[PDB]
Amino acid sequence: GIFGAIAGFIEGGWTGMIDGWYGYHHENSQGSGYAADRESTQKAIDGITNKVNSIINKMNTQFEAVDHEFSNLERRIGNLNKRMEDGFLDVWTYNAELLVLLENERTLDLHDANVKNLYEKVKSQLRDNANDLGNGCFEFWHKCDNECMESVKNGTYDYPKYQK
Amino acid sequence: GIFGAIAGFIEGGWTGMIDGWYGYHHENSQGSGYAADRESTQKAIDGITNKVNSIINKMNTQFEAVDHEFSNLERRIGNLNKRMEDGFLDVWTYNAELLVLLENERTLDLHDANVKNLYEKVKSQLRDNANDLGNGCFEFWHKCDNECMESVKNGTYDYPKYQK
Amino acid sequence: GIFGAIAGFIEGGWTGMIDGWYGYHHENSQGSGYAADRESTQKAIDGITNKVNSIINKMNTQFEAVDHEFSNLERRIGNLNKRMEDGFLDVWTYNAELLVLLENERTLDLHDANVKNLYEKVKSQLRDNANDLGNGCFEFWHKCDNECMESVKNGTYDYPKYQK
Amino acid sequence: DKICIGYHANNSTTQVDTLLEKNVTVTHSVELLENQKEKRFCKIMNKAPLDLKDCTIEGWILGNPKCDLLLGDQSWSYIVERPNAQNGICYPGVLNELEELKAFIGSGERVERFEMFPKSTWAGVDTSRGVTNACPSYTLDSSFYRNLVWLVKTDSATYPVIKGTYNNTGTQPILYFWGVHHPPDTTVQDNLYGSGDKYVRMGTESMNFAKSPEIAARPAVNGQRSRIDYYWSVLRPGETLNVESNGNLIAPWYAYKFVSTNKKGAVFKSDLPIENCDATCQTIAGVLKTNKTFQNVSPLWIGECPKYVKSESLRLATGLRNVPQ
Amino acid sequence: DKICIGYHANNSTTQVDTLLEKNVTVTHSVELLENQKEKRFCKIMNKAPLDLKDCTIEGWILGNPKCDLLLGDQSWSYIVERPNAQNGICYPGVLNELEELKAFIGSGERVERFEMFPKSTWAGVDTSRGVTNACPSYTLDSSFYRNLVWLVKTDSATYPVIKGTYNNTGTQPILYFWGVHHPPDTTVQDNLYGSGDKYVRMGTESMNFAKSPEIAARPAVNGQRSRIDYYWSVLRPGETLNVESNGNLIAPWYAYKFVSTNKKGAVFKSDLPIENCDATCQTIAGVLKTNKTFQNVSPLWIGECPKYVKSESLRLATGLRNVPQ
Amino acid sequence: DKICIGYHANNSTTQVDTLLEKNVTVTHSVELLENQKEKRFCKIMNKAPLDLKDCTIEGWILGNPKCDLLLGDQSWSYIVERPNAQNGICYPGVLNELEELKAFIGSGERVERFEMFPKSTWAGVDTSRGVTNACPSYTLDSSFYRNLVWLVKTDSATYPVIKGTYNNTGTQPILYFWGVHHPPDTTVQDNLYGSGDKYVRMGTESMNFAKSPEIAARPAVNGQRSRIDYYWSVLRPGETLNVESNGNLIAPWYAYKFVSTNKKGAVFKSDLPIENCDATCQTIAGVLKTNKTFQNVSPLWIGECPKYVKSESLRLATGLRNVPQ
Ligand SMILES: CC(=O)N[C@H]1[C@H]([C@H](O)[C@H](O)CO)O[C@@](OC[C@H]2O[C@@H](O)[C@H](O)[C@@H](O)[C@H]2O)(C(=O)O)C[C@@H]1O
Ligand SMILES: CC(=O)N[C@H]1[C@H]([C@H](O)[C@H](O)CO)O[C@@](OC[C@H]2O[C@@H](O)[C@H](O)[C@@H](O)[C@H]2O)(C(=O)O)C[C@@H]1O
Ligand SMILES: CC(=O)N[C@H]1[C@H]([C@H](O)[C@H](O)CO)O[C@@](OC[C@H]2O[C@@H](O)[C@H](O)[C@@H](O)[C@H]2O)(C(=O)O)C[C@@H]1O
Ligand SMILES: *[C@@H]1O[C@H](CO)[C@@H](O[C@@H]2O[C@H](CO)[C@@H](O)[C@H](O)[C@H]2NC(C)=O)[C@H](O)[C@H]1NC(C)=O
Ligand SMILES: *[C@@H]1O[C@H](CO)[C@@H](O[C@@H]2O[C@H](CO)[C@@H](O)[C@H](O)[C@H]2NC(C)=O)[C@H](O)[C@H]1NC(C)=O
Ligand SMILES: *[C@@H]1O[C@H](CO)[C@@H](O[C@@H]2O[C@H](CO)[C@@H](O)[C@H](O)[C@H]2NC(C)=O)[C@H](O)[C@H]1NC(C)=O
Ligand SMILES: *[C@@H]1O[C@H](CO)[C@@H](O)[C@H](O)[C@H]1NC(C)=O
Ligand SMILES: *[C@@H]1O[C@H](CO)[C@@H](O)[C@H](O)[C@H]1NC(C)=O
Ligand SMILES: *[C@@H]1O[C@H](CO)[C@@H](O)[C@H](O)[C@H]1NC(C)=O
Ligand SMILES: *[C@@H]1O[C@H](CO)[C@@H](O)[C@H](O)[C@H]1NC(C)=O
Ligand SMILES: *[C@@H]1O[C@H](CO)[C@@H](O)[C@H](O)[C@H]1NC(C)=O
Ligand SMILES: *[C@@H]1O[C@H](CO)[C@@H](O)[C@H](O)[C@H]1NC(C)=O
């Protein structure tokens, strides 16, 4: 991605985490496990559901062709009608396909950005108390149990305590 | 935002700063105060005024309907005209609304990016001479007066002097 | 750019590097020289060639006007045809110009993002073994020959060796 | 102790396209375009269409004797005319403004057949010899249309001026038909209507009509060298029709009480079967049961259908890039 | 000592929408869509429109006696016809190609009434009895159109062939009108024009015209069982018109010198009032005084108006997200 | 020791526009819009167009004597009519449905002239005096059209009823022409066709036609106070035409075997020269040799052309921002 996260410095994804889009794999004395960041995940979900619903909403009109017949001496107006129907058809096809391609790219960039922002959200809390491997993993210097990992997860990590 | 700045790690905004979009709140011996970074601000202003003017410019055509009347035996061509007018109306409505939604999102992302870029522009100058709180604030180790803050503001902070 | 790289903290570009878009200028005992990162470069090339080809592809229809003549008592249908041709012409002109402006902006943002991502790709490998000047240059503490620079270039820099 | 940050992945092999990249596998996507149709004609608004069967709109509406299956009242959501229906205008001629007539019947919902002019409206002529081998019924080799009547001079005397009147005092418009007979020579014209110049004239509040015969020799069609100029009109509520002719009149007999829909209305030329099913969207190609936004089946429909489009697929990515390992 | 980086905020509660998010408050936005209109008709290019008042385009242009308020020269930026104007075609009949006539007058700017054929152009007939109770003026129960003349045979003798000629030696096109009278029976036809077959013929360099009467009994409209087929044409600069008739001629009397705009031109069917004000944009719904790009008032306009659109609001965000605290 | 990260730059001064910024120099861009044209008419599909030269479509197709250069078979990719061609309809009159005729010939590819009715088809009349000073050839002051024949009564006796028949047993449609002569008075009509009421009638399987003369005095055009109503039709494969007239008949003589293209087909009114060159795209403004997507030359074309658009330039940026120093 353009934020470098997805398929970048975080080279791969976890088929283990099945309860969200973005999350965590911790590792300590009580054992490891996967758990998703429901906050940023739900933000992305609402945003994207909104994007899709907005698109479907803006696409809710229909140009309508007709079964109208034109005689032998009505060549011109018949061809006029055909040209019109075709024309509108062309513009709606274009609008559709283009909008799809564009929005797809931007959506992927969005996910990438969310991952990067989460990584930064973490790195801003733990500064000296851990070791940045550079691949989205941080190796503690001190110890961290369950109510320790949980504090980081709900964004309330007390840095001064573990700085010593 | 997607750069994490606005309503992210910089959780809120300053109703105090009324002379720009992006700026500074300093704090020292002579007293505090607010002052906006006119450079990046003016860049954003020119860019966005350009975006708006470009949009208004590209929207400067008008499909024009007509008062034309069609008889009892002119049902087909009348319905043709109606269908055409409606059709074009639909495509312009769509183009308008879609363009608005899209450009709004991208504009917000732009502002976010500007804030992030300013924060980085600062962090790249001061490296050891200050303490990154992580919330867009930096606590000096040395002292900094007015011609000191001003040097940082006009991008000419001498790091070697204050490294000791 | 919005990632701050191009014409930002990397203030200028190198007319010396003529074998790619993004790359390196190294400096050691055997001498300096320019050489482009073919990986990220080729990624950008494929992506952009794909964007252009997609655009050209989606623009591959043509509304077609006709030489049809309308009599003195055919004022209405003639004006109908004119209005239609003009209408479609207007929408295609708009679509074209708008798509161009938009995609140009996004392409520049893409290049910027690639530069930033490369810079980060480098900074994530060398952490203590070099000095970040802040302008996209890194001054080593240890020594680095040719098979040393090359290891960094092909992404296989051994940090533990040179940490001491 | 340590902790890692990452993203979702799964067994999905669903691919999308972007501007920068084609064939890209993602975790969760959605298809906006429908390409599936049930090749049949169903009911719309719980109302069933009208199968014209082996009859064309002309033969139906003019009362062709082999279209007696359609005779009487009809009600439709839409109309289905069959690609090779054989029963239309049996006696050679042209139905003036046929295309507009089709557009008008298309904008319809229901008709009620009624007698507008009993054969007694035409005094002192022969209202019971108006037949031809060109318009047979399934039971005899020489009849005529069910809604028209062919007036011929009494078995001796000349053709007297005949008059008819219908005051539409009702609240519904009246679709009706008449015709001018164009013989092949002078002796036939005399055999049927007698000598002297002939005219056919029809007046309403907002429509007049006057025409004479155009006697000439035409190529044989259905064994007839003659022609008939068929005409149609709508008598509005309050309007009243005066018919006056001294010869060559194919007089209106039965007419229809018409119900205008104000909605679209569609006339489909198709061979698909009509089944006892329901639908909310009905294209000429079949039925669409979808909640999707687009469709690539057909631009011609009645009911509430997705926007027609030429694309094969419109995949939209909702999830992120899939990188399992 | 310390320093902080941040962004603007204010008291603004103005909201916009994005693809990802609805109802989002921002610091500075702009409205591109205008929804405000002044329900009135104003002057365009400092030129005032034409209020047809209790007259329709037909009654105006044919010189209906109750439209004498409109008689003479006119100049307009656009035309306003009133929804329930009563004064149009008083003597029952059809104005051939009426829709095209309206389109043509629409593409106009000015007319100058003049006498094209004085009653002396028609020799040996009665040019002073052509009246009817169907076309009254505000002062008497029996008159006729101001631009036409109804020619009847002299108070004894038969109807002689009459000729007329107008050589348009001027630089402007001439809109003009005539008509064929269709009586209800033979005795009326004889009472007015005498026996023998009748014709009406008109020739120019690029137009010929020939028609006979179509005598028949029609329903009573305005107490008349007769009809008139009204006709209109444009005599181009250099063209010259020959009129020749031996009966049943509603002859042109007054005609107009027409000025083609080359611009749009609009004919509005509306009941809005015309006031002594100015405007640069004029829809059928009213005036738009805006510098905005879009508008949701009306698609029908004359002048320079914003692009019509169906939206309620098109808010564009210029500032950033508002987060005061 | 050290190392630096950066980006490309060069001598390029090529500029593009974005939403945020105008006039922005980049390293590599591409132009999608073509604005260059070769002001000439070339061959399409290795087939050459048809230069009507000093003839209009009317004069060509009716066989005007000064259009004998075009006489016989023709084959075209498209048609070029010259802005001030002088040779069209020489004898004053109107070609009914001319616009549709042009549309039809436009949808064509080839014609083959043939004799459809030899002058012997018309018995007991004078098929060798049908000339006029209004239709001269380059060699004499009085001729007539090459595809029509003007039938006049024999140098004494009256005008007998004449008949003609053509059974189109071929596989190709037949474009053909006829006409009704409209004299200026009674004595001319008598001098040419004799007294008694006259008619012209034509019947096919799917078309009938009946018309009488419309005698009147018209303005002098080409020294003729008379007119001719010209008519055109297509005799389909299997259809057969019956011609019957007792006077005033401008009879068909030569007709064309027509080849329908099914493709677009274009008729250009232009003065550009036709050269011995080839092309794959041909606008009315000239030839486009491009691999580009758009074009701002002309919306009217035949062949495979880029999408027409109003823009001056559509520059697309492929490289990055150029910052040399
Ligand atoms: C009562 C009456 O007039 N009906 C006739 C009908 C008409 O007289 C005639 O069609 C008017 O155009 O003609 C019928 O036979 C005509 C005749 O047509 C020949 O050309 C054909 O070759 C024959 O087979 C023959 O049918 C008719 O049925 O159409 C007789 C009818 O009684
Ligand atoms: C001079 C002249 O001919 N004008 C007559 C006019 C015409 O003769 C007639 O309209 C031609 O169609 O007719 C007028 O009265 C006709 C008559 O119409 C009856 O049906 C109606 O019931 C009566 O009230 C009566 O008016 C006319 O005014 O139209 C007389 C006029 O002088
Ligand atoms: C054989 C024949 O009838 N051809 C005549 C032709 C016709 O009689 C006539 O055009 C029918 O409308 O007329 C020709 O001369 C007519 C005449 O027209 C005058 O008004 C004009 O002023 C004269 O110059 C004169 O030509 C003709 O050539 O058109 C003679 C032709 O032989
Ligand atoms: C059609 O029928 C109605 C009667 O049902 C006619 O209406 C009458 O019109 C006259 C004037 O012509 C009025 O004075 C009467 O009040 C009406 N009578 C009724 C009972 O409504 C109408 O005129 C008829 N139309 C024609 C011309 O035949
Ligand atoms: C209309 O009037 C003008 C005269 O004002 C006529 O023009 C003349 O045309 C003749 C030939 O017909 C020329 O020889 C003369 O030179 C013209 N005279 C003038 C003074 O222009 C014109 O012919 C008239 N049109 C008709 C047919 O009535
Ligand atoms: C045109 O010519 C063909 C003959 O070439 C005619 O076709 C015949 O039609 C009759 C009935 O009318 C059939 O019984 C014959 O079998 C056909 N003969 C051949 C040889 O095909 C056709 O009828 C002619 N059309 C007209 C009306 O003139
Ligand atoms: C974080 O997690 C702990 C659960 O151990 C909970 O008690 C605490 O309130 C949480 N903090 C916040 C602010 O969510
Ligand atoms: C920064 O600010 C000081 C004002 O004290 C000024 O003298 C100096 O020139 C400025 N530096 C730059 C490069 O703007
Ligand atoms: C990096 O470069 C060296 C060349 O000295 C090569 O031997 C080595 O295999 C490369 N590493 C990778 C993984 O590309
Ligand atoms: C896309 O993928 C399909 C197989 O799933 C392949 O056949 C096709 O060639 C691919 N298209 C491109 C251009 O990558
Ligand atoms: C938007 O805000 C308005 C109130 O300002 C509210 O009524 C409406 O429901 C909101 N729409 C959505 C979908 O959030
Ligand atoms: C763009 O550049 C051209 C010169 O190359 C200049 O004439 C023009 O004014 C510029 N347009 C804008 C609005 O910057």
Image (cartoon, coloured by chain):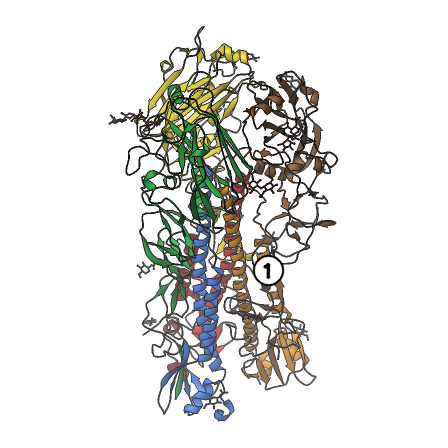
Chain colours: A red, B blue, C orange, D yellow, E green, F brown
Q: Quadrant of the N terminus of chain E?
A: bottom left
Expressed as whole percent of the image width and height from the top left, the position of residue A157 reads 38, 76
10 Å crowding of disc 1: few (<14), some (14-19), many (20+): some
Q: Quadrant of residue F226?
A: top right
Percent position (x, y) of residue E292? 40, 62
Q: Which residue is mark 1?
A: C52
Q: Amino acid at mark 1?
A: Val
* The C terminus of chain E - image quarter: bottom left
- Placement of E109 over or under F122, stated as above or below: below
Instruction: Between residue D28 and residue A46, name the one nearer to us.
Output: A46
Seen in the picture, residue C69 relative to C24 is either above or below; the reply is above
Pick the residue in front: B29 or E279.
E279
Ligand 12 found in image quarter: bottom right
Q: Chain of mark 1?
A: C
Q: Is residue A84 left or right of residue E11?
A: right
Q: Nearer the viewer, residue D21 or B58?
A: B58
Relative image position of residue D260 (x, y in whole percent): 37, 34
Quick check: is the Cβ at mark 1 less than 8 Å away from ligand 10?
no
Residue at the image position 56 percent from the left and 21 percent from the top: F199
Q: Name the element at disc 1.
A: helix
Residue C2 horizontal/vertical position (percent): 50, 72
